[PDB]
Length: 173
Length: 225
Ligand SMILES: Nc1ncnc2c1ncn2[C@@H]1O[C@H](CSCC[C@H](N)C(=O)O)[C@@H](O)[C@H]1O
Ligand SMILES: Nc1ncnc2c1ncn2[C@@H]1O[C@H](CSCC[C@H](N)C(=O)O)[C@@H](O)[C@H]1O
Image (cartoon, rainbow over all chains, first blue to last red; front, side, top):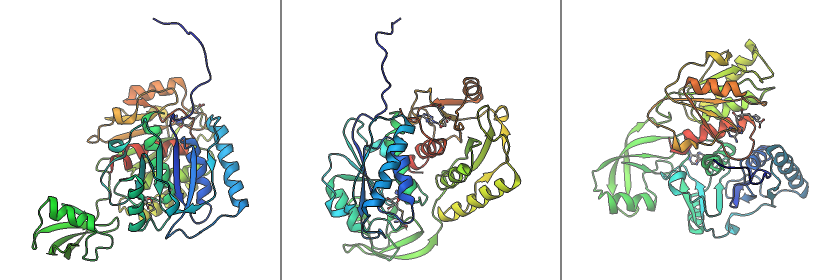
């Protein structure tokens, strides 16, 4: 048996920090990554300018739009915490990470074989052209572990959402 | 052994090179397979270098499929949301997409025009995802017509089991996502009677589109297949 000792507002956050470092993308794609990523529990979205990313910046205006999307998706998903969407930085400026995951076509390691649900999370995804093998080395040097997303080619948007889902939705959090 | 080589240029990355030579003990003449996400081929070691060099014997066909049938049962969604779902499910590996007319789904049917576009989408997405197999997109059917399944996972808000705690990679997969309003209490139960195990996609309410993506990602891309 038991007894309702005290009602409370439901836990909506994932528990640990989840920073998604995503390469700038063509079209409007990024807006969509931000929204869905907000629903999937990301806490920080850090756009990256990389070797093959077409865009290399982002006006103050484009960034404000991405922030309204995050806020709007936050309310829809039932979250109180609004993920911080930041100004794009260089891939070299990627900080050292306690635990990081990078989607790479070559790896064999699955996310469930690598993930420690107790520590913070750093996730990296490349642009439509992908990361340059020197960028993945840089990433591995930062602490990001290369992980597989299957035997099919995924749009960058999907890879980011898929990678994130296996870390949040997949762990039931 | 399958080894990652970006471009199939005949030169292996220092990583794959060390692994094949240091661990698997490769020798000139040793035949192995190379790939990069677009192609696959039978290679023969030419020099251990490093970096190890090889010559391509015969171009191969990359393994693209999940390996088992993956059927997505998705509730009819408003607007063109199902175009997104279809695109993502094709690149994520669904083998068939089955729209369902549910208690809370706004649309209750789908015309020839919509089915055509979704089919056009499946075809394009299969091409862009590298697949040859094109997911079949069937006309909608009532929830009740969902058949008994060998392995079914239904994304339910009121669920607690993780996918990785139930998933059997060897059996075919049947997946179910509800419409914007979500599955009713009677429906989830019915789906559960059909062989579906309710599953959680986390603590936040997700759009039906994102749920299907998440659920599919966890069963395919996640298992590296
Ligand atoms: N099957 C897969 N496994 C792991 N990551 C993948 C993936 N498919 C796509 N991605 C992710 O999505 C990004 C964009 S895919 C871009 C094209 C790819 N670089 C190529 O050479 O064809 C990749 O850099 C990676 O971050
Ligand atoms: N956190 C979650 N866990 C499992 N399934 C979810 C989910 N979030 C969304 N879904 C899936 O996405 C569909 C649309 S969400 C529908 C609204 C939701 N039932 C509510 O009123 O709270 C749901 O039917 C379910 O199939």
